[PDB]
């Protein structure tokens, strides 16, 4: 396979000797006692060595050229594994494959040993990861800044059909990719009081926590650029004896674990400490670099992108430093701050928005609270001048929300202090301007933008689906890997009998590969000839895994009704983690496994229908299941999924999509053509009209016999014999308080699914439609997304120019 | 200097290239941004590389030959720095010195960057360190097993003349010498209950803590042998969500910090957990290795040495495994256990002996308590049979002590379960048999032995005093470095005018070197021509730093009395850490600094007398001050210092000794000749006669005018103007409840000190006496000590044979 680079004779010879050198000197092992894990580490260190030279000169280059620096602040970076990605970007895959083969090792086996760097929950964290890859590939002087959690997203275990959370001790065996930089440790302050003396305010009597950075290299695609992702780790200062030392933990707990609540905002103190910790340490680094290049030029040399409101404290912290430390006057500092910061929103659902209780900020960050009040005061004076007499607008736009307990709306703070605010899909960005942020849009229209999300074609095509990447390259070259729009050239092959056959062959190979994996590491057997129907993403009511469940039960009931009637065989796979304290989400997981227990053991069904719950869904599993999927389920209620990115991964890998006109689904259908998409359900307008009228689920239950039967089955204990009322909460929610209108889209969903089965019966036409999707997936490359951020927000020009080394 | 090895052309060339390779690939740095610390690490990794090959084959060799293995269990390993020691033992010092010189670096400057591995309190921990060096040098298949404390002995800061404790974060910048071995992690159990079912007892419902090993290489002196020191680190098993993860700390606190109480036993639960933790993990390793070589041969392949009673749980744990797990019958298991274990005692003072409350063992280690009761039962049945009717002997020898709260005497447990029990100096070993362990000696005389302590001549001569090592080698060769008895050949040079001059020259150079250091890193100026009077060791009442203080004040008062009378100039240095909760010890430190504040600023005294308190005494400081000392203070009350080892370090480095006939001082004087030692004070017999009579301090106060004046000065606030009664506790203790009879040895001490000053006035005779001490210090090499342990206790023969690589 040519897209994996050349396997030169002296290159292979060099890799082999460095492999054995590391096994000996680095790992300190005998070839007679080395285990597969030891071999993985020897390979990792060998590949890491190749990154060093490039990493050192890339950073040296930025010091010389002194270009504008882009700082991407995120509390999450869902990186996954690093070995194969590094080989791919350095063009070392075939060489390492040959070198290891000659040493009597299977590189694929070694790659499976690496732990995932799961420092994220899902979409938001993975977007940050794809963005880092694209920024390096486009030659931007970019830095990713976050927290080095000792424990990432929990490993999910399914016990008795229930989710069990297990600590993700990903650093147990060490992390060969990172480099600790203790010499660059910085002070972060907490608590204390604010002294107001003759010349300015002073924040004193604070407790100090040190921030120690760990740097991880981020290689661009074959351009010799290697940027940095710097993650901070918490350390206690060195200044009963025993208890005093043991209490050092308290300070170090700040970077101990990733918060897994991606659905409901909880104003926990530890989370606020994490947010300030990353912001305070990062900003000192930014200013340091700047002073080594008049803060008037600060915005010309620095761009700070806030991934959601999680790092929003960057705004008042920048003000604190400029005003309290650098001594700039307020107006000047505010000008600099606004021109430097930009904010990206990822959801319109209210329960996820950060609204911190004032009493918490009052105790932990007294000076920042004062700064926020001043910002609010000046901002509202602006609103009052623009909309005289509109007192209600004043209360609505305030950064401070009154009521039971006063809270600070962090989204309002971000809009006021950013020169750009963006949604992540066209429909989402429009909804922001028409609803949630309407008042702000009317005040400052120029600030609102759209930047449709994307995914990196390196990890999501070349790395996880080499077979498809190869057959594509055979016909249009390899240039598309860094210019995905070139995939449009494949439309001229839609009638090519050879190509149609190859596309279908690779998909079949991926399905057999995954079906085998399912038995090896999970002992479950599936029919490779069935349609692989998959929905993988975090469990949320808005994502409607429940609607999928209703269809599965419908299919099952129809079979029990007419057993000898032919139906297209299906393997329905659903996977995803539920936030620990999200009761309903945990009940849905139990429902899925319960359905499987019934369906998978019914003799009449045979191998015509299988329901499997994919355990511990994470980046490394996504790389395995996505290339094997036939049907991608993207069925969120219209207006709820900001963008979605998994949808893009499926489109690029040869799966057809069944979904609502929500998030990026709208743009995907626009690019490929609605005829090549399985669209169904209410549009956003329909949802609003239903809300005006009032959603009454009982209506659908009374008019749809098939739906009624399912609800009765759930209620009577058909799927829970030993515990008849096990799913009472689910039924109760669907019937009386379903914010996401599951029943409203049921009929159209089922009908649409029938059209999917009909097309699958015609192999040739199914594949031709697949080609039309792959061919038009170009717009969804994160390289396109990053280019827009660069030109329209950060003010820099991307570069595909190879670096000097 | 020839004893530093050869600096070959291609050897130097190789070191240089590997140095730059590590700076680039390992540290990931620019030569334009590298700091001294970066250079130190590059050098360390370069030297470490040379250890690897030898380390791997040494361990491979033991697997092949399968010799009897020696396991040295200690909760303390006071290692100090590792770089220079490694170079010395590998004969790479001159080569590295040349290589670094050519790179434009000063190797001495780089060596000062390394942190000390301070995993010990003092003598006991440092003995373990010297023992590891000697066992490797003598070719024994030995393993050091302990705990990898994240925080070693605290760094001592002197604030306002008071000791302040600062956490010793020695791993902050990383430890290049160790190699984590997560793949060899083992389970350690705590709490739980004991089930008694049909076939044997069962320990169930326990809480598990994992023990992760870290291995550090221990190189022998130029024999290519590299043994291992394996230190265990505590890890929590992976099986509110957030709080559950944060609570993992609780389990990991076991290996967090070294207990600094080397004076008073405190039955703290955390300390007991540490003791079992090291024992449980170590024993699994021992058995594993054994089964890979009938437990009847266990004692022929394994020897376990217990450094004090700290790891005494090894006895009942070995029984637990043999009986409960391997299913051996009690008597057989006990036979194996006794033949495998040996115990070393380090003190006769009662407050330091471990006597664990039964209720603590009952909760934490229920099965071990049962085993201890059974051991006690069977042991006492033996005593009853040997001494029929002696009921009092029964209560005295019991492992269980009655009273307020029942406790387990760990020393009694060690004697019952060991085939050998030894003291650490002849006088100490005799005292054990006549007093503290008299009953046990009468029951089993064959178990009691003596093994006089020693120090390694590599670190304590070659490494810290190259100048002296060189002038010695010039005349008798270099063979003495691994056969210290050869120093006796120097007696033929006692009248050699050339040698006398060189010995005196090196001492003068060391004093100027130390005097300079005192100003550089401490800004205090001293007179290099004065007699360097030094007492460095942990602060304890029994060590009598107070007696030294009384002499200093006496000297000061005599000068104020006759200012224009000539007196031999002196620089009195006292250093050492005080256990955190040892009030009296902390008061003595304050007293020393207070005396300095007065004496050091008195115009009349001039540079005739200076009192300096050496801050943060530790191994690296000992290596600096000892070679610069003229007079070694070893003045413990006769019968209290088991052996002492600092005394041996001073003797080997050209200092004369003033001390009591206590511990090893007795043997040192015997070897060098009493005429070449400044002996004074009560012998052990005198102390007992005084106790019979009753020690009344008032008697000395009334009969000695000079002493009375000092006490009155302390009481009146002469040394504490602002706080007149600051030292009331000290005076009160000296006058009414001094267990160590400070006043009783005052007169003889002062008189002896006068004879010291008299000899110092005759440079030539002082030096000749010095030569007689150095020449007879051979017996105190730890190589001699280890050879005796090997032959008389472990049953193995030492070997000076170079290894094959
Ligand atoms: O993944 C998240 N959000 C979180 O994971 C999250 C984590 C911690 C929180 O406190 C709140 C949300 N949002 C997701 O970010 C993706 C990239 O823009 C979008 O495509 C998805 O539509 C959106 O739901
Ligand atoms: O150093 C100690 N003891 C401790 O450091 C200690 C540490 C923790 C404890 O719980 C009790 C004692 N003992 C010392 O061990 C040396 C080597 O045998 C002897 O030469 C000294 O005379 C003796 O006092
Ligand atoms: O003062 C300096 N002199 C020379 N090079 C420097 C200096 N400061 C930074 N650099 C270079 O710039 C890189 C960027 O470091 P950073 O951005 O501060 O982490 C460093 O690794 C050096 O190559
Ligand atoms: O099963 C085995 N086969 C070959 N060599 C072994 C085996 N077990 C241990 N060794 C060798 O013995 C050394 C001792 O390992 P340890 O004493 O168990 O830590 C290992 O590094 C290997 O060189
Ligand atoms: C791409 C990805 C996501 C986001 O999926 P959506 O379906 O857009 O919610 C979540 N988790 C993982 C591991 C991913 O790879
Ligand atoms: C040798 C040594 C000791 C033991 O000294 P003694 O005088 O025998 O108590 C204590 N601390 C350090 C750092 C040592 O090097």
Image (cartoon, coloured by chain):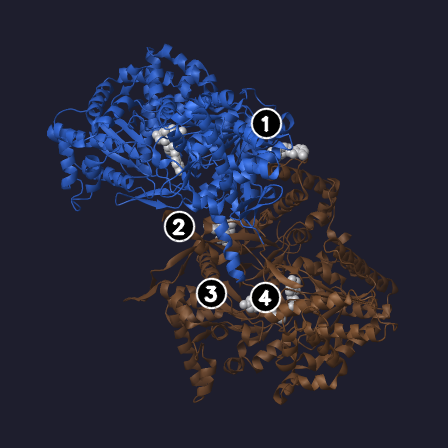
Chain colours: A brown, B blue
The answer to whether marks 2 and 1 sit on the same chain is no
Rendered position, B596 above or below A603? above
Residue receiving disc 4: A579
- Ligand 4 shows up in which quadrant of the image? top right
Label 2 close to label 4 by CB (< 8 Å): no
Q: Residues within 10 Å of mark 3 (few under 14, many from 20)?
A: many
Q: Position of residue B334 (x, y in %)?
A: 54, 31
Element at badge 4?
loop
State whether label 3 is within 8 Å of ligand 1. no
Q: Chain of mark 3?
A: A
Element at badge 3?
helix
The Cα atoms of the two marked residues, 2 and 1, are separated by 42 Å
Q: Which quadrant holds residue B590?
A: top left
The answer to which of B48 and B428 lies nearer the viewer is B428
Q: Residue at x 65, y 42 (%)?
A: A38
From the image, state whether disc 2 or disc 3 is nearer to you: 2
Residue A161 horizontal side relative to residue B156, left or right: right
The answer to which of B159 and A327 lies nearer the viewer is B159
Camera sees residue B73:
no
Q: Which label sits on residue B301?
A: 1
Residue receiving disc 3: A272
Element at badge 1?
helix
The answer to which of A305 and A350 lies nearer the viewer is A350
From the image, state whether disc 2 or disc 4 is nearer to you: 2
Residue receiving disc 2: A243
Rendered position, B792 above or below A43? above
């Amino acid at each position: 396979i040519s897209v994996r680079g050349l396997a030169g004779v002296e290159n292979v010879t060099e890799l082999k000797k460095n492999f054995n050198r590391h096994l000996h000197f680095t790992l300190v092992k005998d070839r007679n006692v080395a285990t597969p894990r030891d071999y993985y580490f020897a390979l990792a260190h060998t590949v890491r060595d190749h990154l060093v030279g490039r990493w050192i000169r890339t950073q040296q280059h930025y010091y010389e050229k002194d270009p504008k620096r882009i700082y991407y602040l995120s509390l999450e970076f869902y990186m996954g594994r690093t070995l194969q990605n590094t080989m791919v970007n350095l063009a070392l895959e075939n060489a390492c494959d040959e070198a290891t083969y000659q040493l009597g090792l299977d590189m694929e086996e070694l790659e499976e040993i690496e732990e995932d760097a799961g420092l994220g929950n899902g979409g938001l964290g993975r977007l940050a990861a794809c963005f880092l890859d694209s920024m390096a590939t486009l030659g931007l002087a970019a830095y990713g800044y976050g927290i080095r959690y000792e424990f990432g997203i929990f490993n999910q275990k399914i016990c008795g059909g229930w989710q069990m959370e297990e600590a993700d001790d990903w650093l147990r065996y060490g992390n060969p990719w990172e480099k600790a930089r203790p010499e660059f440790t910085l002070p972060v302050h907490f608590y204390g009081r604010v002294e107001h003396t003759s010349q300015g305010a002073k924040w004193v009597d604070t407790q100090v926590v040190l921030a120690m950075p760990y740097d991880t290299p981020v290689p661009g695609y074959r351009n010799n650029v290697v940027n940095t992702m710097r993650l901070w780790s918490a350390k206690a200062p060195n200044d009963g004896y025993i208890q005093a030392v043991l209490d050092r933990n308290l300070a170090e707990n700040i970077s101990r674990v990733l918060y897994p609540n991606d659905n409901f905002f909880e104003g926990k103190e530890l989370r606020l400490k994490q947010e300030y910790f990353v912001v305070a340490a990062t900003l000192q680094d930014i200013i340091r670099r700047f002073k080594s290049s008049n803060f008037d030029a600060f915005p010309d040399k620095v761009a700070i992108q806030l991934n959601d409101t999680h790092p929003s404290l960057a705004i008042p912290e920048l003000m604190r430093v400029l005003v309290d430390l650098e001594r700039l006057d307020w107006d000047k500092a505010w000008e600099v701050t606004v021109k430097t910061c930009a904010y990206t929103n990822h959801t319109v659902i209210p329960e996820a928005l950060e609204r911190w209780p004032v009493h918490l900020l009052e105790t932990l960050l007294p000076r920042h609270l004062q700064i926020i009040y001043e910002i609010n005061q000046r901002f509202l004076n602006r609103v009052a001048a623009a909309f005289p007499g509109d007192v209600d607008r004043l209360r609505r736009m305030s950064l401070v929300e009154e009521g039971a307990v006063k809270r600070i709306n962090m989204a309002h703070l971000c809009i006021a202090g950013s020169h750009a605010v963006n949604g992540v899909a066209r429909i989402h960005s429009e909804i922001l301007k028409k609803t949630i942020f309407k008042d702000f849009y009317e005040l400052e229209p120029h600030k609102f933008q759209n930047k449709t999300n994307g995914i990196t074609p390196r990890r999501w095509l070349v790395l996880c689906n080499p077979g498809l990447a190869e057959i594509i390259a055979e016909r249009i070259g390899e240039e598309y890997i860094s210019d995905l729009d070139q995939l449009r050239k494949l439309l001229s092959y839609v009638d090519d009998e050879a190509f149609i056959r190859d596309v279908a062959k690779v998909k079949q190979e991926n399905k057999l590969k995954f079906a085998a994996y399912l038995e090896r590491e999970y002992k479950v057997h599936i029919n490779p000839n069935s349609l692989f129907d998959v929905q993988v993403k975090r469990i949320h009511e808005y994502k409607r895994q429940l609607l999928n469940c209703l269809h599965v039960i419908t299919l099952y009931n129809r079979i029990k009704k007419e057993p000898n009637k032919f139906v297209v065989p299906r393997t329905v796979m659903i996977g995803g983690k539920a936030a620990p304290g999200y009761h309903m989400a945990k009940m849905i997981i139990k429902l899925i496994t319960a359905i499987g227990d019934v369906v998978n053991h019914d003799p009449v069904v045979g191998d015509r229908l299988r329901v499997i719950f994919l355990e511990n869904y994470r980046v490394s599993l996504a790389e395995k299941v996505i290339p094997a999927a036939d049907l991608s389920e993207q069925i969120s209620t219209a207006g709820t999924e900001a963008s979605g990115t998994g949808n893009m991964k499926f489109m690029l890998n040869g799966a057809l999509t069944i979904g609502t006109m929500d998030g990026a689904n709208v743009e995907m259908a626009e690019e490929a053509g609605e005829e090549n998409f399985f669209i169904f359900g209410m549009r956003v307008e329909d949802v609003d009209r239903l809300d005006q009228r009032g959603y009454n689920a009982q209506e659908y239950y009374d008019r749809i016999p098939e739906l009624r039967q399912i609800i009765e089955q759930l209620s009577s204990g058909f799927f829970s014999p030993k515990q008849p009322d096990l799913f009472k909460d689910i039924v109760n929610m669907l019937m009386h308080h379903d914010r996401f209108k599951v029943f409203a889209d049921y009929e159209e969903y089922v009908k649409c699914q029938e059209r999917v089965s009909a097309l699958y019966k015609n192999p040739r036409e199914w594949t031709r439609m697949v080609i039309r999707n792959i061919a038009t997936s170009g717009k969804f490359s994160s390289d396109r997304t990053i280019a827009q951020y660069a030109r329209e927000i950060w003010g820099v020009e991307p570069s595909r120019q190879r670096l000097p080394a």
